[PDB]
Length: 164
Ligand SMILES: NCCOCCNC(=O)[C@@H]1CCNC(=O)/C=C/C(=O)N2CCC[C@](Cc3ccccc3)(C2)C(=O)N[C@@H](Cc2ccco2)C(=O)NCc2ccccc2CC(=O)N1
Image 1 (cartoon, rainbow, N blue to C red):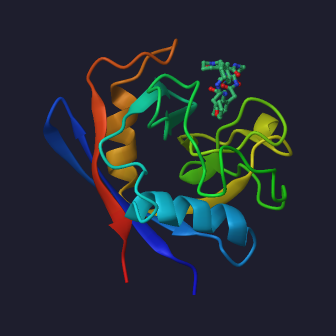
Image 2: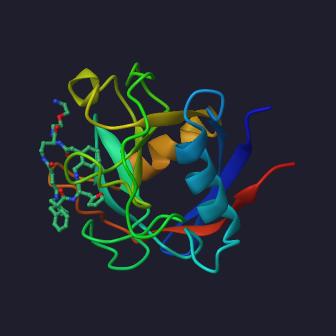
């Protein structure tokens, strides 16, 4: 069955609640496994303690740069980067979980959660899951963003892992 993972998120130390994500291992197993392992921290690194560094209302909330905290860094469990697995799943609406990148075949650890349908990213970013619980928490994160993406509070993934 598809893995379920969680992000517990805070803003300036105040808990916002839990986001639960279903990872579509049935369609993108390699991309799902990378995210799952970065949630559990089992390789010795991952999302715990890192930030949503770029949050743009009516677009998406971006996170996963646990090395540089600014959209330039991150690393996968497969080495630094890994290729785009497929573009089967589309950016259909709020709650889509997809890989951030810097062009083709540059996936590492950065990811985003959409707050709208972002169809112009179809075929360019690998979609690999969806929010199943806690979209209200995603909307709280979104509320601390701005047009440039700079956040007005430090938004931290306080804890994360797999629900089994
Ligand atoms: N109309 C309503 C809504 O409208 C909104 C319209 N805006 C949209 O569509 C916008 C329009 C186009 N601007 C952008 O590409 C924004 C770029 C941006 O912020 N950099 C800041 C961080 C560094 C940069 C450049 C750099 C430097 C060093 C190393 C690698 C790269 C640039 C980057 O590129 N780092 C990746 C992250 C990443 C690196 C490695 C793995 O991951 C990044 O952030 N990629 C951008 C991105 C991330 C997640 C989802 C989508 C998108 C596309 C997007 O943001 N597209």
